[PDB]
Amino acid sequence: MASRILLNNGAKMPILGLGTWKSPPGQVTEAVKVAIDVGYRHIDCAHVYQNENEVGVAIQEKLREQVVKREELFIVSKLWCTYHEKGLVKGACQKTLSDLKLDYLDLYLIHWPTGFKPGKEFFPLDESGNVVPSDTNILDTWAAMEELVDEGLVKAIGISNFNHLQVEMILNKPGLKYKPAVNQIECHPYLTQEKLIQYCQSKGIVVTAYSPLGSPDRPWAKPEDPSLLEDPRIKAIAAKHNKTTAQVLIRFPMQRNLVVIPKSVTPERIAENFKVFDFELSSQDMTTLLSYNRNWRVCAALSCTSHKDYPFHEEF
Ligand SMILES: NC(=O)c1ccc[n+]([C@@H]2O[C@H](COP(=O)([O-])OP(=O)(O)OC[C@H]3O[C@@H](n4cnc5c(N)ncnc54)[C@H](OP(=O)(O)O)[C@@H]3O)[C@@H](O)[C@H]2O)c1
Ligand SMILES: O=C(O)COc1cc(F)ccc1C(=O)NCc1cccc([N+](=O)[O-])c1
Ligand SMILES: O=C(O)COc1cc(F)ccc1C(=O)NCc1cccc([N+](=O)[O-])c1
């Protein structure tokens, strides 16, 4: 399969990237170095992950070593919720650029549609534990993102965790200058996202699947929870193809025309997870994997469920 997908800004994006949420700061530099050595050309980052400085050390060292050229890398980061204000967006992007030791990002996403009160705390709370919103709306934040393209800080802009009505709100924005290039959403066999994916693809927006292995290291995992990597039905498809369960879980979104960003800090898994370009799942395999949907969503925050822009009350 071709390694890159064409975005609606005219640039090509590698369909396989390395995730970095939860990658410890003392391990992520070597994880990213190994990833680049074994062929990864796309790294998914965020300020809220608190490890961009260490990701940046790896990127810079591989550029200095001339393992890769900057134009061959596709570096993604995200604007955190406490920076949705007009006057804060550029500085938030600049801090990410400084930490990653880059002069531009290939793609910068609104991380969540929910804006929060600015300040030091990433989740400002009231005394009952509700997140404290900011009055900013998704359209003014979008205008601020467009300015970053026009200032040369980012080559593409997009969104993450937007439901179809929130995507539509931007597409219908008066005076829209740049369409979102990407919507990055949770997607795996237990949360297959058909409706939102078809909506986005019909509008020319590329979808990136996050948590493709079900995020088994998420901090709120419970022992009894569903496990994609241990599902015997997925293991059987993997065995039939002489691949690992993770390799099937990564190839699955690729064949839906999605980008996919599995996370690992384990060098042998980083290399394993990249070995997915030389086998195909049949149409029957694909439909069988889709049949496992249970609307099982792993990534959301209870503190945000009354925010006016909370994305997951809508069906899709
Ligand atoms: N936009 C958003 O709101 C958002 C939300 C969630 C995630 N994301 C992005 O998506 C990335 C991926 O999602 P995620 O981190 O939630 O989880 P994930 O990629 O679904 O799963 C990561 C977990 O799978 C393990 N793993 C990786 N390869 C494996 C293999 N071959 N065999 C067995 N276990 C394997 C990792 O272990 P080891 O690391 O110990 O090897 C880790 O515990 C994130 O890191 C982040 O970049 C974005
Ligand atoms: O958001 C991510 O990329 C992964 O999840 C997190 C990563 C972090 F470093 C810290 C927190 C989270 C987390 O709780 N993420 C979930 C989340 C965030 C913001 C808004 C909402 N919401 O439901 O509106 C949900
Ligand atoms: O709520 C958070 O901040 C992170 O997510 C959890 C934290 C926990 F301590 C326990 C469970 C979760 C959890 O299930 N999170 C995923 C989730 C899916 C769908 C809806 C919600 N919600 O909060 O409305 C949350």
Image: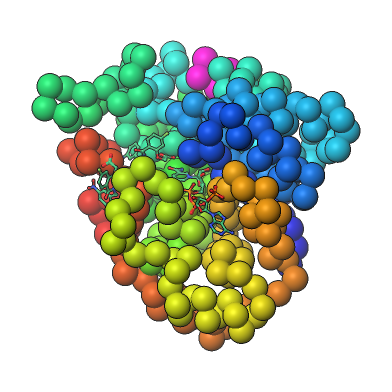
The single residue placed furthest to the left in the displayed view is 128
Work out whether 316 lies above or below 231: above
Task: Tell me: 262 left or right of 223.
Answer: right
Foreground residue among 233 and 5: 233
Q: What percent of the width, then of the height, locates residue 25?
A: 56, 29
User: Residue 208 or 166: which is nearer the viewer?
Assistant: 208
Residue 11 on image: x %, y %:
71, 45
Count of picture labels: 0
Where is the C terminus found, in terms of image quarters? bottom left
**Which quadrant holds residue 106?**
top right
Residue lying at the far right of the rendered structure: 66
**Residue 226 placement, left or right of 270:** left
Measured as percent of width and height from the top left, residue 96 is found at 57, 23
For the point 49% across and 59% down, the residue is: 213
- Is residue 178 at least partly visible in the picture? no
Which one is in front, 34 or 2? 34
- Residue 285 in which image quadrant: bottom right
Give the residue at x 45% y 69%: 230
Magenta part of the chain: 90-94
Q: Is residue 36 visible?
A: yes
Indicate yes or no whether the magenta region holds residue 93. Answer: yes
> Secondary structure of the magenta portion, mostly?
helix
In this rendering, the answer to whether 172 lies above or below 279 is above
Residue 80 left/right relative to 270: left
Of residue 138 and residue 254, the one placed in the foreground of this image is: 254
Q: Is residue 260 above or below residue 87?
A: below
